[PDB]
Image (cartoon, rainbow, N blue to C red; front, top):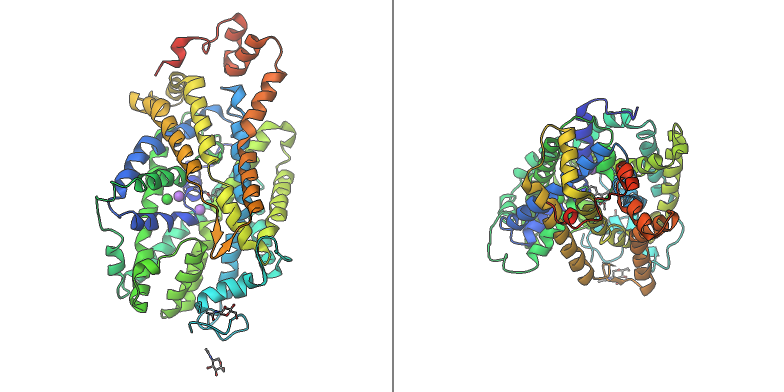
Length: 545
Ligand SMILES: COC(=O)[C@H](c1ccccc1)[C@H]1CCCCN1
Ligand SMILES: *[C@@H]1O[C@H](CO)[C@@H](O)[C@H](O)[C@H]1NC(C)=O
Ligand SMILES: *[C@@H]1O[C@H](CO)[C@@H](O)[C@H](O)[C@H]1NC(C)=O
Ligand SMILES: [Cl-]
Ligand code: NA
Ligand code: NA
C-alpha cells in the first residue's frame, strides 16, 4: 500500500518537469557559443553516452526495485547509508535559496500588468543621476528599485527584509505546501500544466523572435563548427561538468519518483525517453535566446559577445529590454514571466518531495502524519529563506549558489555508484533488473556501471577541487569568512558518510569479522551470513563484471 502513481503519464511528466529548470534554457546555448558551437556537441555526446545514461538508468532501476526513498534503498549495503542523508541535505540546501528567483519572477509578473513598463526609461525615484537613457535603465530598475542593492555594503551589512518580496515568498510557499500535502495523488495532476506551459510559451517566443531583423545573424553565431577547439583542455572539462550537472542525479528525486512505480514496468525505455527529451529541450531553446540577442546586437551596433550575459542578469535585465521595444509589449512580458514562474515551480516541488519521502521512509512515526511534516518542512524553508530577501540578499544568493550544490553532488554520485557496482555487484543488479523487466542488461551497461563511470566521476571531482575560484558579484570581493562558511556548508553536506559509517560499525556486536560481515553484506543475505558464507569475503566477487 505504497500509493503508486494514478497514471503512468504522471511519472514521466513529473520527471520531465523536475529536469527542465530555469538554468536549462540558457546555460547550454551559452556553453555551445563559447566553446566553438556545433563542434562542442562531440565531447558532450561522448561523455553523455558513456556516463549520463548509465547513471540515470541505475538510479531509476534502484529506486523501482527497492521500493523505498533515497536513504531506504541502502539495505543492499548498510554501511553506506549516509549518502542518502547527504543527498537529502543537498536538496534542502538548494531549496533554501531556489525559492527567491520565483519570488522575483512573481514580482516582475505583478509589475508587468500596466500600460507603461517601469524599466523603459530612468525618470523615477530609483535612478542615479548618470544613466544611459552610466548603467542602463533596465539594470538600474532591477538592482535599484527591486533588490535595493545600493543600500548594502556587502554580506556583512544586510539590513531588514523587504515586505514586497516577503509577500511573494509567502505566496510561493503557500502554493508549494498545497501542491504537496496529499502525496503523489494530487502532485501528479499539477504537473499536467506546469510541465507543458513552457513549451507553449517557447513556441510563440520562437515564432516572434525568428521574424526580428538580425535574428539570423544571431543564429549563425550559435551553430558554426570549428573542430580546432577540441585541441584545448577546457572544452572537454566544460562538457564533462555540464553533463554531470545537467541531469537530475545526485538529489534523490529520481529514487523517490521511481519508488512509486509498479514493480513490473520497463524503466529502460522511460530513462531513454526522459533523457532524450531533456537533452533536446535545451538545444531547441537555444534558438530563441540567440535570435533575440542578435536582434539586440543589431539594434545597438555591438558584437553579440558583449550582449550575451549570464546568471540572473540575463533573464531579468537583457530579456525584458528587447520586449519593451516590441509592439504589444505588455502581453509579451506577461507571458514571458508566466513561463519563467512555471519553469521553476516543478523543480522546487520535486526537491521538497525528495526530502519528505526520504525522511518519512526512515521514521515510521511520520506516517499518516504527512500534512504536519510537510507544514513543518515548508515553514522551516520559509524561515531560512528570509536571508535572501534583505537589502544585500544577492550576496547570500550568490554564495549559496556557489557552495550548496558543487563538489558534493559528484562525491555523492561517485559513492553511490561504487556502492551499487562494487559492494553489491553488477551481476546482482542485472539479476534484479531481469526480475523486474523481462530482459537482462548487456555487457556494455555493466562495463559502464563498473569501470567507466567511477573513473570519470573521480576525475571530475579532482578537477573540480583543483580548479577553484571564489565567487563574486560585479566588483565586490567576498571576505575570508564567507569562503570559510561556504566550505563549512559543503563539508557538512559531504561528511555524512564517515560519521554514519563509524556509528554503524561501532553499534554492531561481536568481533571485527562479524561486524564487517554484517556491515557490508545485504540484508537479504542474512541467513548466509549467519551460516558463515559471505560473498564479499572473496577475491572472485570483486573481479566479476
Ligand atoms: C541549483 O538548482 C538546481 O540544481 C535544480 C534544483 C532546484 C530545486 C531543488 C533541487 C534542485 C536542479 C533541477 C534538476 C536538474 C539539475 N538542477
Ligand atoms: C523626465 O521628466 C521630465 C518631466 O516629466 C522631463 O522634463 C525630462 O526630460 C524627463 N527626462 C527623462 C530622462 O526622461
Ligand atoms: C553614477 O552615480 C552613482 C550614484 O550617484 C555614483 O556612485 C557613480 O560613481 C556614478 N558613476 C558615474 C560614471 O558617473
Ligand atoms: Cl542542460
Ligand atoms: Na522545472
Ligand atoms: Na537541465
